[PDB]
Amino acid sequence: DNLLFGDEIITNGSDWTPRPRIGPYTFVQQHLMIGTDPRTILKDLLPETIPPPELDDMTLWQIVINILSEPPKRKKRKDINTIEDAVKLLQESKKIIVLTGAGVSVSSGIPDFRSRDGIYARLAVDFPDLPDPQAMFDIEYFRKDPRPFFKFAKEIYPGQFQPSLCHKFIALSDKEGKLLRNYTQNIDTLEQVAGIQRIIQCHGSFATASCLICKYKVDCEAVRGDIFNQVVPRCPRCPADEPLAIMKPEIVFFGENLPEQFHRAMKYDKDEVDLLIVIGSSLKVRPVALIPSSIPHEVPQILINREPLPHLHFDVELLGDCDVIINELCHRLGGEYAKLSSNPVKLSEITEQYLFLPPNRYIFHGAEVY
Amino acid sequence: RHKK
Ligand SMILES: Oc1ccc(/C=C/c2cc(O)cc(O)c2)cc1
Ligand SMILES: Oc1ccc(/C=C/c2cc(O)cc(O)c2)cc1
Ligand SMILES: Oc1ccc(/C=C/c2cc(O)cc(O)c2)cc1
Ligand SMILES: [Zn+2]
Image (cartoon, rainbow over all chains, first blue to last red):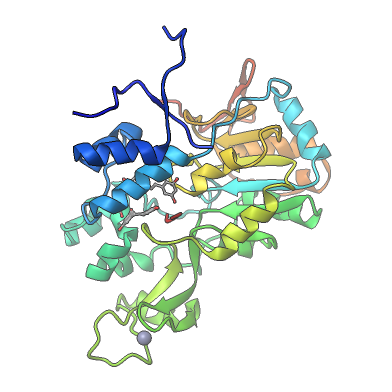
């Protein structure tokens, strides 16, 4: 048996008497002594996801210590509630961090390579070894067989997509010099195309490719040929006999470290930002999902997503399609913001109207709290 | 320790 009773609270850095407190290392120590399966604790902390089987037990434990060590979630600031408050913030603020996800590329026409009915349908049909869409970006599977990734690559390649209202909005805030940084999890490289200057591409992009062995870098235009013919692009230097000599695009696959430029940028912007805005991301993947909990709690946070975030407390929640909400905010902002679109032939048949659900919530078109 |  073990020393722990299960009611302990694990601290990092009716209940009328204090519960015992353990460190995450002490906790995991105990569970090692019992020899409990880490997958269990992992399923208790994260019930909605299964760790890939190629994970050694010790790694899983390291992941558990990680999870247990994560910062305290932010208490919603009751000063800030309304969309009015929100625009007042977007005007007064001087060092704004914008955290984006696929929601800023919805209007751009990029297929859902994250859903199970998108490209994943035909790909799964062709490669039945693929468990789920995310495996398309699993580094171990890629090593094993990069075919599905490149059968898929040409579908989302950086040559044929146009920026959204959101991109343009962010780029404009950058011109005006209010944008401290735009952290994006997108790999579509549209942030650049829209002319945002201070971007950090947290999960990489198709901008370059690099051999798996010798780290030989090339431009996206060097590999574009092989990719559009659906041929796995090989390395120039590496001997042909070597099979893993593949030009892998520099997007952060699952199980890979994020670029050091990211961690640097976060350590800097950590104590400078005066407004955080999450746009078009539900924040499911770590460590990026940790960012809102990582900045000073007094900094106001604003959410612009299709769905609320259960695991996170924002001051103002605008729930709906991103471009719609952004458009609304533009109209309230005036100036170059109101002037901001070149594709409003599709925003003229989408409701301008929203419904306010006190004190925080606003429901726009394209929202789904299903 | 901070892998994606
Ligand atoms: O099954 C799972 C496999 C991997 C993970 C990743 C967890 C994680 C937690 C952190 O605090 C930081 C981080 O970089 C990663 C979670 C569950
Ligand atoms: O919140 C979530 C965070 C991550 C994931 C992806 C998991 C995953 C699935 C695979 O088949 C392979 C892999 O390397 C990772 C799913 C949900
Ligand atoms: O501290 C850590 C944080 C994260 C990880 C990642 C593990 C991992 C490995 C894979 O092949 C796929 C995956 O989806 C996740 C490991 C240690
Ligand atoms: Zn090579």
